[PDB]
Amino acid sequence: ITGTSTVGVGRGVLGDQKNINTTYSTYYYLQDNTRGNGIFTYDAKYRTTLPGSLWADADNQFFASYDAPAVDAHYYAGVTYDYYKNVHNRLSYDGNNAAIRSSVHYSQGYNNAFWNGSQMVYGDGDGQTFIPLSGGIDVVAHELTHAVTDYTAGLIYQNESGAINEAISDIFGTLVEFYANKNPDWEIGEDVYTPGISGDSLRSMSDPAKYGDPDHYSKRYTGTQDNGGVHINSGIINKAAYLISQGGTHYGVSVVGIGRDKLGKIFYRALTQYLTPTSNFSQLRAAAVQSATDLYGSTSQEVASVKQAFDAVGVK
Ligand SMILES: N[C@@H](CCCC[NH3+])C(=O)O
Ligand SMILES: [Ca+2]
Ligand SMILES: [Ca+2]
Ligand SMILES: [Ca+2]
Ligand SMILES: [Ca+2]
Ligand SMILES: [Kr]
Ligand SMILES: [Kr]
Ligand SMILES: [Kr]
Ligand SMILES: [Kr]
Ligand SMILES: [Kr]
Ligand SMILES: [Kr]
Ligand SMILES: [Kr]
Ligand SMILES: [Kr]
Ligand SMILES: [Zn+2]
Image 1 (cartoon, rainbow, N blue to C red):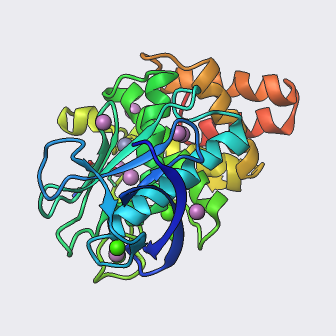
Image 2: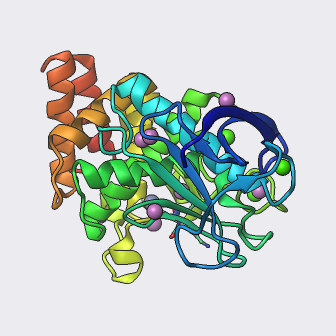
């Protein structure tokens, strides 16, 4: 909508207060004009017609419980935009500041979130498996990273290329969580998953096996459910990325950690310059090795650690 840029205030899903960029024209809208072509947040009103209505509020205060998922979808899309711009010189998901659109209150008791090819969509959860999923910054950034992948490598969402697609979203979802630096970790979705259970998450990058996901190529799922295991076999790549950053010894193979920033640079370069729609795990290893070589040199510690990490998870 055409209007003047304003700053509202509200509370997110977890009860934290934050300021949000809004737009005023009779109503205050969740329309952030400060980032690219805009960040826009919509109300799906418990239905599945998308995007729904651009979020309108009478007084620029967003403290109602119904407001909370919108506040966080809006705010964390902003954080994610800032991450890609400041850390990777990427302007929104298409690199040309495409508008970022999100819808909240999708369906009823919907225990998921997704990128639908055009926008982000967040369920409210059923209150037992999930609370509203935009409450997790790693979730928001995971979903927006699917948009980045779709505009860059274009990894096909099945089998090994799909597992890489998923892992890329977990990796950068996690790196955005560290960037915002509010109790960050190497777990996925812990802030919105099972409110009645402390200390768990949907997936773990540090130990995928904790939730039954493979941490080695020899343990890969080869069946047909979950598009050939895209959320399952992602654990193999998530573990490799974790090892590259943090180091460790895994099935007897020791990896020297090189830290999160370099992990991010190596994988962002692989994603945008080397991976293709059909890339498999072996081809990811090659892309990561060549990316690290480009950035740090063929005899660098960084290249050695990438190789160690993929060795550790049995890839090549
Ligand atoms: N996002 C993952 C986990 C969601 C679990 C929903 N109960 C998937 O779609 O497989
Ligand atoms: Ca209000
Ligand atoms: Ca956290
Ligand atoms: Ca996390
Ligand atoms: Ca929990
Ligand atoms: Kr703001
Ligand atoms: Kr944007
Ligand atoms: Kr949209
Ligand atoms: Kr982005
Ligand atoms: Kr996620
Ligand atoms: Kr939760
Ligand atoms: Kr497994
Ligand atoms: Kr795999
Ligand atoms: Zn995903």
